[PDB]
Image 1 (cartoon, helix red, strand yellow):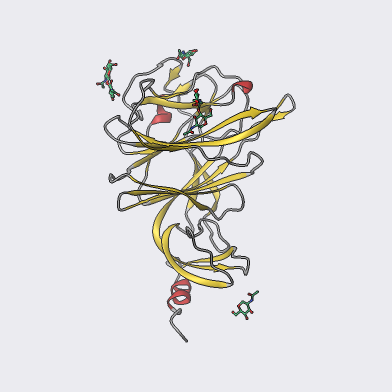
Image 2 (cartoon, helix red, strand yellow):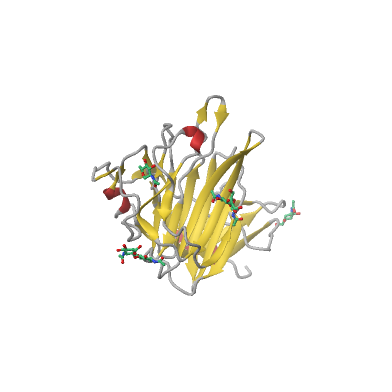
Length: 288
Ligand SMILES: *[C@@H]1O[C@H](CO)[C@@H](O[C@@H]2O[C@H](CO)[C@@H](O)[C@H](O)[C@H]2NC(C)=O)[C@H](O)[C@H]1NC(C)=O
Ligand SMILES: *[C@@H]1O[C@H](CO)[C@@H](O[C@@H]2O[C@H](CO)[C@@H](O)[C@H](O)[C@H]2NC(C)=O)[C@H](O)[C@H]1NC(C)=O
Ligand SMILES: *[C@@H]1O[C@H](CO)[C@@H](O)[C@H](O)[C@H]1NC(C)=O
Ligand SMILES: *[C@@H]1O[C@H](CO)[C@@H](O)[C@H](O)[C@H]1NC(C)=O
């Protein structure tokens, strides 16, 4: 259970489909993976020791993507899918460009980040939305942070052209609710992978994003004043045979040594707390 409202409680079984897939690759940041750009600041032809919310070198990712057709498992909405959100998380999300009847699409899972997922708290929801404008497929990314009455079994659905045996249903507030924040963000539907930093500090939530390269740019920030404790990558139901990936590794507060081209491109990094070599390599930045 995520919310605590028995919504459209049909086509649900208790089927064990296993546990989120572990990546064969670990976090290695030795040229950018897991780093972000500084908001309203651009460094050229220089290194820079920097504290921040970075993923842990040697840590694996987990594929939190859940793909359904009609049936949802009750086990999909518990640990280990309903996961702890501490400092933050880093996401490598695949843009599933399923090709059907000539046209190419752009599906990937929604993620909700909250405390209790009840209308008494706020919950962040980062949901993709696709639509055609004269047969050209457009990418949106509907961010919203609201006092949602979340369902026990929240799921999104794919584009209706790919076929759906379920209606989209994650919250039941067809009555208009109190929201701290909501705006849409366009993304390039021709992107191989989308990357996200989601972290919190002193009651403020932070989001970084990129649909080009792996190094994320700043997206938005929002003062909650509360402390976020959980994330859930929602199952996406579809008739078409999509191949979903939402790869997540957690963030902790760490010092990194970053490096920039003359064109301001972060091209190299050192996980400074990973290694006795790395520690030595950073601390030696004070005038020798
Ligand atoms: C806030 O959420 C709670 C549950 O988290 C809702 O309570 C349910 O209300 C319906 C009436 O429509 C009852 O049939 C259920 O038994 C209630 N459930 C529980 C667990 O109490 C409540 O309606 C929501 N209210 C608003 C305004 O969003
Ligand atoms: C984000 O874009 C979507 C594009 O559909 C907007 O959602 C629709 O808003 C209209 C109101 O003009 C409603 O009639 C539709 O029911 C909405 N559709 C969906 C799928 O939610 C939305 O307005 C945009 N959000 C923001 C914050 O601008
Ligand atoms: C309720 O859910 C079932 C299966 O998920 C679906 O067939 C039906 O159309 C849904 N209807 C409404 C109004 O939610
Ligand atoms: C970059 O900085 C170095 C010194 O570390 C300097 O010699 C060089 O002129 C600079 N190159 C560019 C491309 O800015």
